[PDB]
Length: 84
Image (tube, rainbow, N blue to C red; front, side, top):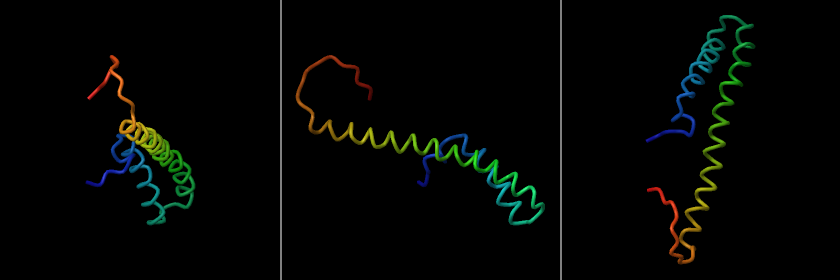
């Protein structure tokens, strides 16, 4: 099951459409001015990938530490909120 960090977000479809307009326009050579415009809008659209993917990467690092410490954790019977 292939699913990249941002591919699972709804905002990725807006990116995929914006980058498609760019890659199609540059491949077809329709208008040299449209390339410069769509390159600039692509940087905004692609940045949403880097933004979400950075959040998921950082969360993974912190959550991995939270799972590791749970094996080395001391034995203490205290009433805490535990989700499952």
